[PDB]
Amino acid sequence: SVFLFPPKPKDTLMISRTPEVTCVVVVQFNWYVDGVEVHNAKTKPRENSTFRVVSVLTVVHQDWLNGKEYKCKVSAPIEKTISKTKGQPREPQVYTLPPSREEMTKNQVSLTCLVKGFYPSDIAVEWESNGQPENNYKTTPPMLDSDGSFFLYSKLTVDKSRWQQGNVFSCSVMHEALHNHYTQKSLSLS
Amino acid sequence: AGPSVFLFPPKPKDTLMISRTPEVTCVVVDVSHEDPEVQFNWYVDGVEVHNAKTKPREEQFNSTFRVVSVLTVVHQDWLNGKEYKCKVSNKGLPAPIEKTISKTKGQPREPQVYTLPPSREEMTKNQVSLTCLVKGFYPSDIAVEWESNGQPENNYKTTPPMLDSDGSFFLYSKLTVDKSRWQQGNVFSCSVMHEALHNHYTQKSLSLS
Ligand SMILES: *[C@@H]1O[C@H](CO[C@@H]2O[C@@H](C)[C@@H](O)[C@@H](O)[C@@H]2O)[C@@H](O[C@@H]2O[C@H](CO)[C@@H](O[C@@H]3O[C@H](CO[C@H]4O[C@H](CO)[C@@H](O)[C@H](O)[C@@H]4O[C@@H]4O[C@H](CO)[C@@H](O)[C@H](O)[C@H]4NC(C)=O)[C@@H](O)[C@H](O[C@H]4O[C@H](CO)[C@@H](O)[C@H](O)[C@@H]4O[C@@H]4O[C@H](CO)[C@@H](O)[C@H](O)[C@H]4NC(C)=O)[C@@H]3O)[C@H](O)[C@H]2NC(C)=O)[C@H](O)[C@H]1NC(C)=O
């Protein structure tokens, strides 16, 4: 039983990150990029009541994003192929939404980042404030909208005082269809 | 293997509204032509009941029978965590198949329902987003609806419940409307039904101020 995993969307969209294709078994590994075999992989030695072998292949950001195919050959040998999710790009629209008046009775409040109209669904979202990450968020998986694009929401939970004091919070979105693969929107008390 | 059994719970909305009709559904697929007879026995907290409604077997395209038994449940019984058991008997089985279902367990928490107007920035578009945030709820079983002037809205999508940091769930429901409808002061209403709400129902409305 072989399972081939794609890079995380954020890794492909940030040059500083290292996108990887993972070939998981639950052994000779042969890796192919558009048919052409490559010797780049890092196979770790075979580590409950069963065995597991893992090979990891580092990919070039642009190659992954331009749709090159990545073939893991677990050596009848099981051969598998992966590449970027297909579809014509649609640029995300990003909107920040303050907490409801009625949430102000609570100790913590909800800062909302709506991301809609994007295609395909490979996307990353982060928050920051004052030059540091704000990690107390949950982001919904992308969901198919009625027009065939995706949407999601990210919810940053923040101490109510931090919001009342006027701190500016920022929702950062990364997607292949954005200019520079990045955009940001900010939100503060108004 | 031979025949297999699937047990479906009632819809959350059906359990929460006393006028509606919550049902547990027991489905048997892959019943052979050779041994086509099926018996359902139904149990509520391990006590056999005899009021289920069983339909005659139906021939499928793949030359197998499908047989369905439906048990109507008492709303409060389901909400009070009673266990519903379907036992399926068939001569093609090494032993009868038993399956049990009940409401997700765990301390209930009341959903908080907030409506959020469109971003000012979205106002440059032809269509606008109305957001209903529902958070702090347990269990995840929930129904959410958008309406205007007592009439259902045709363009909305609700995210599946997502686990929050404290073990409760949240979701968002996005309503898309023509910008003019928002501009002309129309009232839009997000209704939520959940076991931990008073009367299992709450509605929150918003309009351009
Ligand atoms: C012969 O044909 C019949 C009929 O085939 C049907 O028509 C033909 C023309 C084709 O198009 C088929 O694709 C089509 O299905 C076949 O019968 C099917 O058999 C399979 C099993 O092999 C059943 O699969 C199960 O499906 C349920 C969900 O079922 C709903 O959704 C279906 C499609 O979306 C729909 O067709 C069904 O009617 C049903 O709809 C629901 O019905 C209820 C009752 O009326 C209703 O109230 C609901 O509102 C309604 N739902 C919707 C969305 O409208 C799925 O949940 C099952 O998944 C479990 O089992 C899998 C293994 O079988 C497993 O991989 C999953 O992970 C999951 O496992 C369970 O997981 C939970 C934890 O979450 C755990 O608690 C359990 O222990 C665990 N394991 C279990 C339960 O074993 C499953 O996929 C089809 O329902 C069934 N179709 C019908 C109509 O009954 C038959 O297989 C064919 N035979 C051959 C040899 O080919």
Image: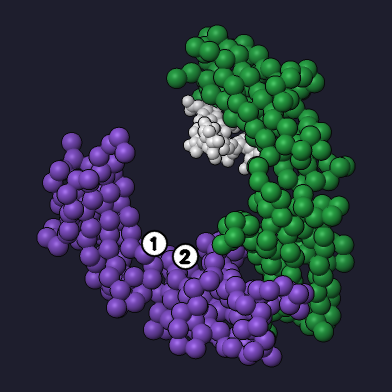
Chain colours: A purple, B green
Question: In the image shown, does A99 or B88 lie closer to the viewer?
Answer: A99
> In the figure, residue B172 lies in which quadrant?
bottom right
Question: In the image shown, does B193 or A63 lie closer to the viewer?
Answer: B193
Image quadrant occupied by the N terminus of chain A: top left
| Secondary structure state at the residue bearing disc 1 | loop
Residue at 80%, 82% (x, y): give it. Answer: B208
Image-quarter location of ligand 1: top right
> In the figure, residue B159 lies in which quadrant?
bottom right
Residue B11's spot in the image, x, y percent?
72, 42
Asked if residue B22 can be seen in this view, the reply is: no
Residue at 63%, 57% (x, y): give it. Answer: B168
Q: Amino acid at mark 2?
A: Ser
Q: Are marks 1 and 2 on the same chain?
A: yes
Residue A85's spot in the image, x, y percent?
39, 61
Q: Which mark is residue B184?
A: none
Asked if residue A88 can be seen in this view, the reply is: yes
Question: In the image shown, does A52 or B144 lie closer to the viewer?
Answer: A52
Image quadrant occupied by the C terminus of chain A: bottom right
**Between discs 1 and 2, the one toward the N terminus:** 1
| Secondary structure state at the residue bearing disc 2 | loop
- For disc 1, the marked residue is A85
Q: What is the C-alpha distance between the residues marked 1 and 2?
A: 8 Å
- For disc 2, the marked residue is A121
> Does residue B17 lie above or below A139 as drawn?
above
Circle 2 residues within 10 Å: few <14, some 14–19, many ≥20:
many
